[PDB]
Image: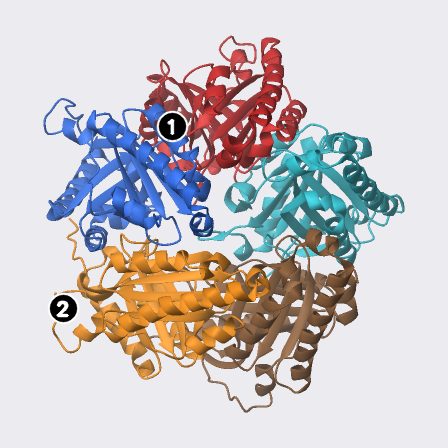
Chain colours: A blue, B red, C cyan, D brown, E orange
Amino acid sequence: RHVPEPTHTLEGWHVLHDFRLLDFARWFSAPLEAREDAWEELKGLVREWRELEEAGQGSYGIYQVVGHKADLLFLNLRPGLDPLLEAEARLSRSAFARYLGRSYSFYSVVELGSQEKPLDPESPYVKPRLTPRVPKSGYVCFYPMNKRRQGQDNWYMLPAKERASLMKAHGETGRKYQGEVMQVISGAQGLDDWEWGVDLFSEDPVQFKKIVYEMRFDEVSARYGEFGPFFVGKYLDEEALRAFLGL
Amino acid sequence: RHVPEPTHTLEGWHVLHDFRLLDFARWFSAPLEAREDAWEELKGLVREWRELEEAGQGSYGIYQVVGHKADLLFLNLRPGLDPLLEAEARLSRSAFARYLGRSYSFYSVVELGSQEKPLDPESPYVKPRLTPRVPKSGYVCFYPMNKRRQGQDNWYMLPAKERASLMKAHGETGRKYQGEVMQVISGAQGLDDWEWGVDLFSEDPVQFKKIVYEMRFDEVSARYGEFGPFFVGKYLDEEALRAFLGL
Amino acid sequence: RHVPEPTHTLEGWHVLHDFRLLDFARWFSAPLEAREDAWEELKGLVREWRELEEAGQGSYGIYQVVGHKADLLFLNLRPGLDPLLEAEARLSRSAFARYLGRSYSFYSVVELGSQEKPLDPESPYVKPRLTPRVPKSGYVCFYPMNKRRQGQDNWYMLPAKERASLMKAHGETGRKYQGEVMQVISGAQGLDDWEWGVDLFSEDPVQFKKIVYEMRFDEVSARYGEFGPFFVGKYLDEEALRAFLGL
Amino acid sequence: RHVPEPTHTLEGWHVLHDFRLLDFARWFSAPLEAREDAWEELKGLVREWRELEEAGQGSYGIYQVVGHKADLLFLNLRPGLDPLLEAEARLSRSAFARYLGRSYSFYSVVELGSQEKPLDPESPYVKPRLTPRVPKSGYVCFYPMNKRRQGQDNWYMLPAKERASLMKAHGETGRKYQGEVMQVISGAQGLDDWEWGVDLFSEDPVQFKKIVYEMRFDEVSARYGEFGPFFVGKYLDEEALRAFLGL
Amino acid sequence: RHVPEPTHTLEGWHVLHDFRLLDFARWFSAPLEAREDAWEELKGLVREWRELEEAGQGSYGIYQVVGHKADLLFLNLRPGLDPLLEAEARLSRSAFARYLGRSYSFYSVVELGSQEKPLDPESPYVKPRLTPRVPKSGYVCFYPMNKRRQGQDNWYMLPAKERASLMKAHGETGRKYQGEVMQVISGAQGLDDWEWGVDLFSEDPVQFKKIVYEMRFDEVSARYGEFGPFFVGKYLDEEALRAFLGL
C-alpha cells in the first residue's frame, strides 16, 4: 500500500496579514481634530509594534496597496497567536479603524520545510530564518497558495524523493534573485484557507513579476502550483503614512 | 453492476457553529450604559447554556477568532435541532447582537463512523464520543470537508474494504497527536453545504498545523480530501470575553 | 451519430422557494405598534395562501431556517408562475419585509420523470404526485442539484437503459425511508441556476442526514450527483411564527 | 499542425440585458406623489423606446423577474453600443432608478452563425433574423453560455464538419418547438463574461423547461454546454408595470 | 528530467485599470454647488494626467463602461508603480469619488514576450511598444487572462519551441485586424490575480467580437486560454464626460 513520507517542517514566528480598505470619503471629510486624534493613536500603536521588534519579539510592516483589493496592509509577526490577536484587536478598536473595512486577511506561521530529513533547529544556517525581520523600505508581494492534488498532478501522493528534487530545482530558480528579492514562506495548513502564505520583498516591484513568471516554468509550479490573489504594496514609514492620510 | 456498501454511522448531539463579526466602531463608541446592559444580558444567556451543560443537556464554547472571516465563534451542542434554533434565535435577538454580523455558520450532527463492522453503541470508547463536551481552555480549529467524487478519485464508489484500509491509516497517523489534539467529527450530509464538520481542540494552535499537514500525506486525504475554510479561535472564559469587549 | 433518448417528464405545480434573513436588531427594537401592524398584514397574506391550499388550489409552508444562509423560508406551490410572482412581490411589499433581506430563492416545477416508458398523467399512482401538499408539521430539507456532465461521468450522454438502471437502484435505496421521509422533486432546467430542486420532509431532521448520506453511495449519486447548498428548516404554524417574532 | 476553421458569423442589432432589483421597502414607503412623479417619468422614457421600435430602429421589453436574482429586466436592442449606453444611462438617471439596484447585466450582439458555409446577409431567410422584435406578451428566459474547452470536450479544437453535424442535430431537436418558442442568439465574445447570450420567448414558461431539458441530451449540449444563470420573467405592458409598482 | 525554458520579457510602462461604479442617485440629486466643485476638481486632476502624457511621461484614458460591472474606467500608464499609486489615491480622495464605488481594478506592466531569445529593447519594432499611447477616441475592451495548466493542456510545461509555434499562429490570425484593432498586452504575474491584462482599442466594438471569437479557434487559445471578465467602454473626452455627468 501507499507509504506516506510527510514533509518535515520547523515553525517560527506566527504571521498575520491584515488587509483593509480606507473609506476615503469619510476620512478626508472628517473634522481635522478627529483625524489628528486618530493619527496620534495610530502612531502610538505602531510605535508599540516597533518596540516589540526592538525587543526581538516580532516584526511588522505597513504598506499602501495598489488596486481595489485593499488599500493598507498591516503585517505583523509574533512568537504566537495571542500576541497577534492582541495587535489585531487593538488596531480594530482604534479610532482610525472606524474609517477602515477589512477586505482580506491571512493567518500563518513561518515555515522551513525539508522533504526527506528533519532540519536542525539550532543550526546557524536554519535558526535565523525562523524569525524574519520585515524590510523597512521597498515593496511587498503577498499571495497564498496550495500544492495541487488533482488527477495525475497530486503533490501529496508523490514520493519524498521526487518532492525533494522538484523543490531543489525551485529553490535554485529563486536563488537567481539572491540579494534582489527576499522570500518568507509561511504555512497555514489547518490555520487558514490556503496551505501557504508567501511574502516577497524587493526594492522594485518588477522583480516580483520577473521571479513569479520565471518560477512558473519550474515543474513544481507548472504542475503543482495553485495560486490565490496577489497583493502588491509599497512600504510606508511614518511620514509616508502621514502623507497618504493627508495629514 | 455496482453494489453499494454504505458507511455505518451513529449520531450523537446536534452541533451549531455560529460565527459572527464584531462591529468594533459601533460597539466601542456606544454609550457605556448601553454596553454594560448588553453585557449583562449576554451573561444571562451564556449562563443558561452553562446550566444546560452542567445538567448534561449539551455543551458550548465561545471563541475569539483570528482574521477577517469571523471575530467570535459561538459553538453549541444539543440533543436536537430545536434547542439549537432556540440558542441561535436568543443570541440574535440580544442587544449585543445589534453590534454583530453573521459571517458563517454550520449545522451538523456528531457522527461516529465505521466502514465495515458496525460500532458498538454501548462501548465505553464509543458512547462518550456521541456527547462530546467542549474543552474550557486552549484553542479550536474548525473546518468543513467533503469526500471527493472526481474521476479516478471517487470515494463513494470504492469498496467498503478499501475505504476501511484508507481510514485505518488515517487513524494511525493521528494517533501520535492524541495527547495534544482532541477531535470531534460531525456529519452535515443533508444538513448543510459540506458533508462533515471537523473540530480540533488543543492548547497550541501549531498542533493544528502539524496534524492537518501530516494527514494530507495519507492517501485518504491526498486523494479524497476536499477542504473548506479553516477558522482558528482562542477559548474565552467570562473574564476573557469581558476584556475583549473592553469591559 | 449520437441518438438522444431524452428523459420523459410530467409537470405539476410550479414551486417557489423564497428564503429571507431577518434583521433581528431592527425588528426587535422597532416600536410595538409597528411590529403588531406588520404582523397583522403578514398573517393576512399567509391566510390567503392557506385558504388557497384548503381549496386544493396550491400549497404553502413557512419555516424557521438554521444558520446564516436564511432565517425564514416561504414555500409556495401554484398551478403556474404568475401566482408565485405575486407571492414574492406581495411579501416584499409587506411592512414585515422592511425587516427582511432576500438571501436565496429557487423557481422550479414539480417533475415526475421516467427514463424509458412514458408515465400516465391520469394514473392513480402518478397524478397525485403532480400536486403535493406541504406537511403542516415537522421539518424540511431543501437542496438544488445537477446531473454531472464531466469526462467519463456524463449523465446526459448515457443510454436511457443505463439511466433507468441507475434510477431504479436509487429508488430501492430510498424505499426504507418511505414512512419517514416525503420527497418532492421539481425541475428547473431553463428556469433557474440548477437542473432540479429537491424538498425532503420529515418529523426528524436526522432522517435527512441518513437518507442523503446513504444515497451518496448509489452509483447514480456517487458518479453523477452535483449538489448545491442545503437548507434545513422547522415548520412554523401561525402561533410558532408569532412567538418567533416575539409577539 | 492545427488548421483553424472559425465559425462564420453575421452581426445584427446590439443587445443589452439590464437586470435590477427593486428596493420594495423604500419604494412603497415613499410619498405617493414622489412615486407618481417617478412613474410618469419612467413611462416617458419607455414611450421613447416604443417610438424607436415603431420606427424600426430597435426593440425593447420590460419583465417582472422571478426570484432573488432580479426583479425587473429592461431588455433593449439597438443598431449599436452608443444608443444602448444612452438608454442605460437615461434609466439610471431616472427618479425611479433611485429605488433600483443593478444585480446583473449582459452586453451582446445578435449573431447568426454557420460552421461551414458563410451566410448571405441579404437572404430573406437570414436578413430578418438580424433585427429581431421582442414579443409584446408572454415570458422570457435568459441565460448566457460558453462552448466547453476542457480535456476531450473542446469545442474550439473540433473540425468545422463535426461542429456542423453537432449543430444540425441541435436544430432538429428544436424544430419541434418552432410554433411555441422564439429564440434570439447573441454573441458576447470580447464583449462580456460569456461567449453567448440566449433569449427564449414563449407564452408558457413550462416550454422553456421542456426545450432546455430535451436539448441537454443532444451531444452538442451534453458534452459542450457550459451554462450560466437562468432568468425567467413575465412580459409587462404599461398597465402591468404600473400595477407591479402599486400604482 | 524536465528542463525549463522560461519566456524572456521586456517590461515597459506600468498600467492601472481603475474601474468604478457611479452612484447615479446620489450624484444627480446632489446640490449643484457640490457637483460643480467636484467636476472642477476632477478636471484639474485629469489635466495633470493629460500634461503628463503630452510630456511623453505616460498615458491615460477615461471610458464609459457598459453594464453592471463598472460605469467608468480610469486607465493610466506610468514609468512605475509609485505614480500609479498616486493617481488612484488622488482620484480616491477627490470630491467626485465620494459618488463612486470601486468595482474592479488591475495592476500590470506592459510586456513584450519572446519564447526563445532576449528581445532587443532598441529595435524600431520593439521600443515604441514599451510605451503605448492610449487612443483619444473609439472604444476599449479589457480582459485579464492566464495560460492553462491543467492535465494535458499545460502551457508552462511545453517546450519553448512549441510555445513559439503556437504564438506565431496566434499572431498570423490577428494580422487581418492590423489597421482596425490596437492591442496592448501587460503582464501581472506576481502583481495581480491574473497572469496578463489585455487591452484592445478600436473605433468599432464589433471588431472586439470578431477578433476574440476568431482567435478562440487558434490552438493556443482553444487549449491554453483561460479568460477573466470582459469590459467594454467608450472613450470620453472632457466634453463627453461633462455631458455624462449631467453638467
Pointer 1 chain: A
| Along the viewing direction, whichever of C145 and E82 lies nearer the viewer | E82
| Residue D69, percent from left and from top | 61, 55
- Secondary structure of the residue carrying numbered label 2: loop
Q: Which amino acid does label 1 sit on?
A: Leu
Badge 1 and badge 2 in a common chain:
no
| Along the viewing direction, whichever of E138 and A137 lies nearer the viewer | A137
Q: Which residue is drawn at 78% across and 43% down?
A: C60
Residue, disc 1 = A85
Decide if residue C40 is on the left or right side of residue E28.
Answer: right
| Residue C18, percent from left and from top | 69, 47
Pointer 2 chain: E
| Along the viewing direction, whichever of C235 and A82 lies nearer the viewer | A82
**Picture quarter with the C terminus of chain C:** top right
- How crowded pointer 1 is (Cα within 10 Å; few <14, some 14-19, many 20+) is rated as some
**Residue projecting furthest to the front:** A33
Mark 1–mark 2 distance (CA, rounded to whole Å): 50 Å
